Image (cartoon, rainbow over all chains, first blue to last red; front, side, top):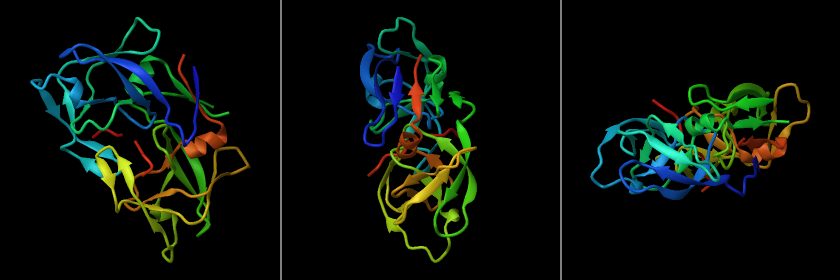
Length: 116
Length: 116
Length: 9
């Protein structure tokens, strides 16, 4: 599909996300060219999982507490696809605000921006 | 142009920005389907410059002091195009780290995100 | 607020 860009309407997709630490789950995620890596809500992992430290640069400056990195890879299936995006690791949002599909995932779908 | 999505090479384009406050400048900007609104560094603006305060939601939560809002439109020229994008208003980064072309502007270029 | 989205290091 061709997603039109529109400031009043976030470009979101339904994705099945597999932490390999609890059963896979379908969540609504923001499609986001301005993200180097994907972001997944901490809520989707067993509250018993190890997670590495990491620093992320956000609109409000560097943060060292807010995102962890995953110990295991994460598989992500998009609508109508058997074959999963595979992410060596990705970011975990400690406050459960965000689900963001980033440039890592989008490379593996071979998504592009197009400016006419 | 078609712009390929890659975690290790940000989709940046050169862009002439006219702040209406001082001569238009060339900046390097990130195309970001996950930005509601465009961001340009405060350094583009003269020192006599009145700007409204604003809230922005970022990776590490809501920031109060980092971004400001313009009172006048901002015109942006993309490479090899004469017609500007005109934004009614846009966000201003006081720390001078973000130059982001958001969906307000990509809507105007008629930009699309395309997933095979 | 409007939202603005994420970089490494």
